[PDB]
Amino acid sequence: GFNCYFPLQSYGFQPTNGVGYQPYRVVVLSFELLHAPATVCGPKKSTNLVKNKCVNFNFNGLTGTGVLTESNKKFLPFQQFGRDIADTTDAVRDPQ
Amino acid sequence: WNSNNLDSKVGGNYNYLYRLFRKSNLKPFERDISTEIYQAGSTPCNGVE
Amino acid sequence: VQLLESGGGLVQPGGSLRLSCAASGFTFSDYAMSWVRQAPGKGLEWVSWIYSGSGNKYYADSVKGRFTISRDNSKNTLYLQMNSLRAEDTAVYYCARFPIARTSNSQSSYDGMDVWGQGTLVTVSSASTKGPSVFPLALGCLVKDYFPEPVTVSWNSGALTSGVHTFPAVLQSSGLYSLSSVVTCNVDHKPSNTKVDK
Amino acid sequence: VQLLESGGGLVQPGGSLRLSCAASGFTFSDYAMSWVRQAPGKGLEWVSWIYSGSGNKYYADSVKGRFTISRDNSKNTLYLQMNSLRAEDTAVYYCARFPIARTSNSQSSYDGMDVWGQGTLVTVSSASTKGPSVFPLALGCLVKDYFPEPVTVSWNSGALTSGVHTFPAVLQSSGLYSLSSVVTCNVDHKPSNTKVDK
Amino acid sequence: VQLLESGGGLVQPGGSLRLSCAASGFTFSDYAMSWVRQAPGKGLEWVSWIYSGSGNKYYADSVKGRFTISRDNSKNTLYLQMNSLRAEDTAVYYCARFPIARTSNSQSSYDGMDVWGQGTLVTVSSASTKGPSVFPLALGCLVKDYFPEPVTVSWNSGALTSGVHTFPAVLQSSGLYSLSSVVTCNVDHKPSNTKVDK
Amino acid sequence: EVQVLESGGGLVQPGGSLRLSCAASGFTFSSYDMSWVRQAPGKGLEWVSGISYSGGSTYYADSVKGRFTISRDNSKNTLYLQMNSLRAEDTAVYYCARDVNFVPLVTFDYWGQGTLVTVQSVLTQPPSASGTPGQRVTLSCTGSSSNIGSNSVTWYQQLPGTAPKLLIYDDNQRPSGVPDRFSGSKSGTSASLAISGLRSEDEADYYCGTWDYSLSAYVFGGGTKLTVLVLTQPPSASGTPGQRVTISCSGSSSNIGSNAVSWYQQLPGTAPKLLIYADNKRPSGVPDRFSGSKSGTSASLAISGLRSEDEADYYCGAWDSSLNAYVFGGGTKLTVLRTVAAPSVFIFPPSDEQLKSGTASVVCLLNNFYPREAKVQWKVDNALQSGNSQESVTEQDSKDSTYSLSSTLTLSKADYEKHKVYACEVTHQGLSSPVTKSFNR
Amino acid sequence: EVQVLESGGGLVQPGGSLRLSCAASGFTFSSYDMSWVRQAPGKGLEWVSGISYSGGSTYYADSVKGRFTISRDNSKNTLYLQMNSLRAEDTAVYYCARDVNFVPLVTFDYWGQGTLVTVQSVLTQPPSASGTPGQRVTLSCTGSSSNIGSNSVTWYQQLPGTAPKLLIYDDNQRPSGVPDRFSGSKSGTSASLAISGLRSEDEADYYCGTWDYSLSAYVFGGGTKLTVLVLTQPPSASGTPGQRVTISCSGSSSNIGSNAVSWYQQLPGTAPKLLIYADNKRPSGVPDRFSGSKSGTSASLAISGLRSEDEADYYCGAWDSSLNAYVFGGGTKLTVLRTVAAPSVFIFPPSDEQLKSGTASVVCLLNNFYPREAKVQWKVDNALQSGNSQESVTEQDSKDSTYSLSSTLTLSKADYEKHKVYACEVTHQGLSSPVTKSFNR
Ligand SMILES: *[C@@H]1O[C@H](CO)[C@@H](O)[C@H](O)[C@H]1NC(C)=O
């Protein structure tokens, strides 16, 4: 009643309404980044592979300079990195 | 510095002027040597004092 | 913002009719609506008020039962069914937009009757109509024996505007109204639908 | 700021003379100057206005041609040559400073007649002067048969000040003015240059 | 805050008695006190004023010497000894709290007579008392021949309240007052201590 | 913020145990005494227990003596009530109240929100007291020389369904946030609260609380649920142009006191224009001179600097909470005080089409005259009309601010020629000498 | 700052090419749609083309369809119009307008300064509309169901020689910087703008712009150049002390409407003092009560709180643009309404000096009397003087605020002794009973 109006009013959405009265669907993308690892990234841009040439490779998070060659190292089906007793990056599984 | 003995003259040293009339306050470090009749009213009077 | 009323005219006593108020220029569903009565040459007498059809409708103490207000938000119209009309209800009805929703920064006639329509005129009388009779007289022209009020009287069809004084019509012994325009005269009577150029 | 006028006195009809207005207390060249006429017991009738000698001089419609205003910024004086004087010009002339230059923060009577001098009195009449004759009456003394107005009348040479009412002089059949001071009387007539202690 | 006076009653001319004003609801020692006289059907006469017993006590010019005001902050009472009473002093005495200490933010009737008690009534007369005589008459009831004023008159012991008009008593030739209540009547005379239901 | 949260209330069974814990923040919890107070559903406050600043001295109500343990851990600044061997009477809502002052002058200012625990009053405060808006109601506590006489009396206003709120402490004072409307009072062994003027927000339960140096408990009061139980406008105000005219209308509390008044300006022949929409505020598009101010029940529309456009009917309208109607004012007819003008007088013999129509309407006119008061008497050759002539005056002119009147005498067709001369005499202040044009047949 | 600079305009020839480039800074240029709009010299705005936020969708006016290419390089955040195969009609000034909203509800808020390129309107907006200061002017756009019927209506105010400025968007709202004075309106296929009250800064061209879902262009409106369209003074105004007196003088447009009025206060016997110099402003050294206000052609001097020092002649003076003269007002004689005083009446027989001089001037005096209206009749033994006595009244007293009058009867030397008694009778409101001292020879 008076001073007791129902809080919600309905939208009158008729096809003959002017554009300012027509139902527009709105999606708001709210982007949140914080200490938690960034999990939703844009489609990752991967370049081509070239062997036997000193390049600045960026296999996933790992970056570095060097020439990369096909190898016989039998990685386990889950391993990505390669390393040695010197704790330096020796080999890498091609991500794609 | 006072310069009465240099820039005064019996009858008036009218060689020195000053600008009473312009539209807006002068911007800092600006000078305007233009002598254009100051239209203080609505009517354009074709540059007659 | 404009509210246009329709349905004002001759009504037999105890009759029934329907005032339709087309409202444009505002979101009709957000503002309450009301009808306000004004007897000829008298004060504003509130008729009724509504916000939602399913909600509570409020009516004047003198019109409870014989009046029915309603909305049509699809048509942006406010309807007033008046039935079993009594004599004192001959008046001018204004369709008034009563804002009831105030927003934060937008301050707008909250709870004030904001905008009033031109208002129609309802005559609750069994007397039949009669075409106006124009008689030329500061040049003047009487318009006598027309029923009912109002009649639109002007000089030279509105061309001559300055000095045109119109006095309110009177209720004569025959019950027939009469005005006069003083400074050709155009007298247009909508209820009898006669346009006279004298 | 003070403007002192000189040159007001007896003038034969059609005569010629020169009002000199010495202006002190302000930069004379920055403000326009004007002469304003006030007939005895009448309103302020603007005479003329000037700002630069080489510019346009403005004159009242009734004095166009017979009056000439001029400046002397070296002497800080405003001069008014009036020639071929007509009868209605017997009056009091005020030298008024008309500021036309407003500055940013300094707001000063821009375009208003700011400061008015004491004003001199010009009599355009062929009648000769005549020394005042005191006629003592609440004590009182009548100064009759003096020409022309004004005469400075006082009680006890200004020592007795409260209750001294002076009424304006009158134009008699002989054309000779008369006042009276009511509560010795000092009557000083400048045009005839007589000081009388009665 | 309430001030209740006691000691108002029959006084022989030239007699002596003591008005006691019990003050509650405020820090008595924080506010000056005063006595104000009101002759029956007359204005208010400032009787006296005090703040401290060691302080000077202000008295009206007509009561200097025959009145003595005092305080008792331990009992929160204000005492007024009136002796050698004269005829004009028959009146109503109000005990009024006169604030004389204003604090920073608390703004309170500083120097204004703030709160007035119900006031007692003192009759300085050698005439003895006489019980009221009630006579039933718009229903009315006269109450005649009672001394002194006041008497509390009511209809149906206060049950019937609307329309009960009481007019002030009069001073008759016998010196005996009389009122009447108009619309059983309850007439309660405190000085003679008689309750009559007629 | 001196808020005191509280928890530990829930469904339990008689004869069990329950730990209530309330945590206080924003103040030095280890310096203020605190207490646990209890309110049975639909019953007055009952003070459970209370613990001092140090936690050394503990006080318990004799109704709960020997079975409730009040405890206080200052390190975490929390305070506990250990309810043991519960009864059926303990089902209530519990609050922990901060004590502003030492005992005996106990003063409970901040209260917990309330923990719903499911499982006689010393001060004989009246069960209820009925008041009216704008009244002066005295609701009086009552106790012994140990309850009221020796210790401070504190008054709490508990709104329906909320924690109690302190109104009066130390028998006289008020907190920072209590209107001066409420006034404490205490005399001997009887205390009271005086509410001068009442509103819709004074509908609450009012409790009187006092410590006891003999009973050693903070006894509360019982209930006392305080219950609260046409826009007359001037017909025609006026003023000279340039003046400030005050149009003051008044209705009731339901009409205008508790609802927003509005002021509308209806010019003659036009729809009204809202000049004021709030009690004070003014819509855009209206000159700033149209001020509005509602004091209590009287709303004033102040029009400053009147002009020829300011003459209109000024209505005040307000919604009614009781009648449920937007009741308007009577309608103030504002007119400007103009210098009295000279009525230009004219007259017209009826035209010959009147004769062809069967009537004769002879008209007399007074144009450009002030004020509204003027009379026209149809002197038909030294004879006065007998209730047949009818006249209506114009409204004040939109620009000239003057009046025009026309008197019409409608006589029979045969009545026009039975007489020879017809004339109209005018009575007005502007023309002491009457002016009349005596036309002939 | 959301400024959008633009360049690339100069002298070219028909049938050539021209690259216009505008650079936008201060906002994400790659997220807002933009457009190129064109204004022929002395003609309404014509919307050239428009490019979306991505540059994917491009829209062109059919007058320039197929020959102008709108392009947008987001890396440098610049936007280009490539004009090819130019015509003579393309000589105009070009702006690039930021689009606040998506299409169709196009909204052009920020505009370029203008590039001068030298080489019909769908919305039938009126060519012009004339308004007056303080008026309520409704200038109405007009379109089809595709222009105004289904698309928002935005109103631009272009001052002479500047870029357009947004006033109304989405048919109702206003930007942050537009006064509420302007109000949008839209009904069916007809939009309008309402200006309530007008000033000197509302002199501009007002255009209505709407997108088209059928024509696929942002059609503008046509022109509608909104145009804004002896000091007769009362002889003697008056009022009681403490009242607010309004002295209203009026001349002409040349006299006072277009020139600054001034108000001067000439006390009796003293030079005038300038109380008001501007239409409203007041010089320092004058009491704040002396207010001034020039509405149109009528200037009002309001003196509030009259006193004994406030009685003087108040002149209004204004320069004439036509007659070339500082024309003053008639001169309002302000006097204070004092309580009617008692005229002290005196009379003096002529002195012997008068006999030695040959005349006899007998004087009668009425001192300290109010008001100015009073009469003196020389009753020389029940005989009245015949046009020989002369009298002048004083001005209102500087402190007592009252009048003094003296009547002098100047008769012959032999006329003094031919009669015995001379007396003066006084007629005034303060003395109903006449008072007269009958001196004898
Ligand atoms: C993944 O995509 C790459 C590139 O298209 C392709 O060479 C490879 O065969 C795909 N499948 C695997 C092994 O993920």
Image (cartoon, coloured by chain):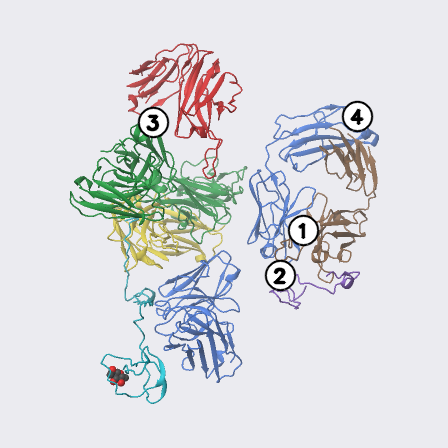
Chain colours: A cyan, B purple, C yellow, D brown, E red, F green, G blue
Residue extending farthest to the bottom is A52
Kindly identify the amino acid type of the residue bearing the numbered disc 3.
Gly
Give the secondary structure at mark 1.
loop
Looking at the picture, tell me which residue is in the foreground, G107 or C139.
G107
Q: Eyeballing the image, is G288 above or below D61?
A: above
Q: CA distance from mark 3 to mark 1?
A: 78 Å
Residue ID for mark 1 = D114
Q: Eyeballing the image, is A20 above or below D153?
A: below
Ligand 1: quadrant of the figure:
bottom left
How many numbered marks appear?
Answer: 4
Residue extending farthest to the front is A85
Left or right, F329 with respect to F124, comes to: right
Looking at the picture, tell me which residue is in the foreground, C89 or E160.
E160
**Of discs 3 and 1, which sits in the foreground?**
3
Residue ID for mark 3 = F188
Left or right, F149 with respect to G381, comes to: left
Residue D161 found in image quarter: top right
Q: Position of residue F138 (x, y in %)?
A: 33, 32
Left or right, G254 with respect to C124, comes to: right
Q: Label 1: chain? A: D
Q: CA distance from mark 1 to mark 4?
A: 56 Å
Q: Label 4: chain? A: G
Q: Eyeballing the image, is E25 above or below G291?
A: above
State yes or no: discs 1 and 2 in contact (Cβ < 8 Å): no
Residue ID for mark 2 = B40
Residue E11 can be seen, yes or no: yes
Residue ID for mark 4 = G417
Residue F229 can be seen, yes or no: no
Q: CA distance from mark 3 to mark 2?
A: 84 Å
Q: Label 3: chain? A: F
